[PDB]
Length: 49
Length: 180
Figure 1 (cartoon, each protein chain N blue to C red):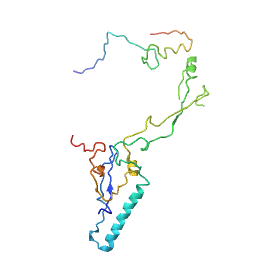
Figure 2: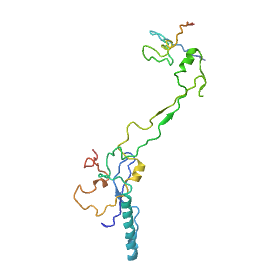
Figure 3: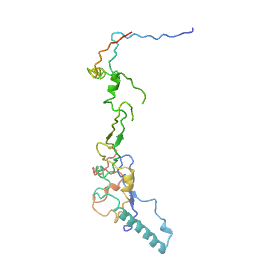
Figure 4: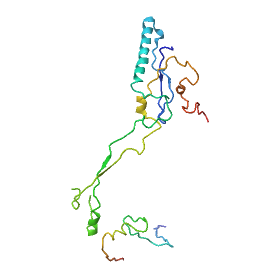
């Protein structure tokens, strides 16, 4: 019989993580792009969808 | 025979870089056996020149050392490689470039840049951190290890012979590390 495939996953038990970084690298407690804003003084908002 | 010897030519080791034990020169001999007196005194007058050229070459060129065929060469007696220090042109000094992005301007592309007037460039050492020891190259074996002309051959005490002419002999063990 002719067929077609389906390709969804499931990854339970953990959390998605987006490290607030330049190259997304966990390089300690701080991040260089994390403490980049103290080099400025911005205090600006965000939107997520 | 003993007086005008056909010289011991060495053999090059490509892996270790040491001398692979020498051998009698058996591939340049004249076939003087079919010659009367007016040429066998001329042929022996030729070999007596290449046994004198090879002694006025061994003084001009080879490093004066005690152990011919040493197992571990020192650092200073081996040709090193010291090129020029690599002058690296840094494109954009980020001490005033990260301030430009934090002002709000995203950059793209890439004096050298128009927003900053300065451009520093550094140099660094291009040689190795330590000089090299233990084994000489091919061109060093071209330079040193001229064919050793061995007069009055094998004419002394055991141990007083050149034991490194044996192409199996460890120079710091007095022994062939053989099948074990």
